[PDB]
Length: 312
Ligand SMILES: [Ca+2]
Image (cartoon, rainbow, N blue to C red):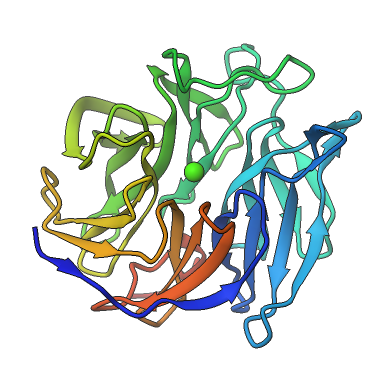
């Protein structure tokens, strides 16, 4: 597999478990720090980063009834400039730019306790596909599916239903939606970290997935595996392979990577493009830091960049 070695430029530093890089509708940049702890208990944070200086501001340090969050993944909404945050203790949060937030679900659409979440992806229809590798949300004792198969997948729909759509993953992690050229969502990709697999499903409709398949194979036998993922504008899927020192690049058909990107650190965790550029922001857990590098082409547009009242 061909490997490329682009220049990585430092963006910011000292962010425990740096994760969830995201741009909002105004171009501001945010990161989550899931692994910040106070007195050994979760006290994770959502940060805004000034791209010009690298300075960090904590906008939200979410807690519900004294249970601190482990915010781990983020996407920006389209119709309002607000962040949807996957939290390993609190489930799914919606966080405003002013730092206020709401916890969306204690239970799912069937009344089962919600599980703690790690990453999420909006499709262009506005449905939010979410990985849930933790066990039950606070106040339940914290557990996660690194060793046993109890991780789940949800779809939080436009009509506000939190629907469990699959179960029994060993640490479902990154997630992404593939769209037809006309914008129709049609494939969901889910990383399963320790098994070194990417799984696919056909998206038949909102919260309707079928044809579960082992879509992609992640190199290496290190502890870790696929963490976050992002599509480029040609539907290549770039996947942080935590523990391998590389980001893998899969072509549209999956299988084995067609290219790797060597990083100057062992533990890439997540990645996100700056809108309308080739610049990918990458979080990593060797140094607990954020970097950027130039890819070969622009990113796939996220839902927040599309227009509700568009014509074309
Ligand atoms: Ca993750």
